[PDB]
Amino acid sequence: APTYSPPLPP
Amino acid sequence: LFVALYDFVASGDNTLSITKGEKLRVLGYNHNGEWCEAQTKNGQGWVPSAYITPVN
Image (spheres, each protein chain N blue to C red):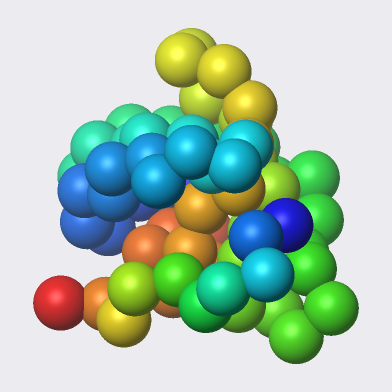
């Protein structure tokens, strides 16, 4: 998985 | 079996673009549960866990 966090839900 | 709640555009790095309403199959999650490895008709890759939910 990416090491950065995903975007927050809108 | 899951459905996408919101659109998500892939940011590369084995992420997967998904569209609100698409069906997905979940394979698992990363270490903190923020990312989900999923399969759709478009391929396989990581999507935000919060952008999908079980359906049926």
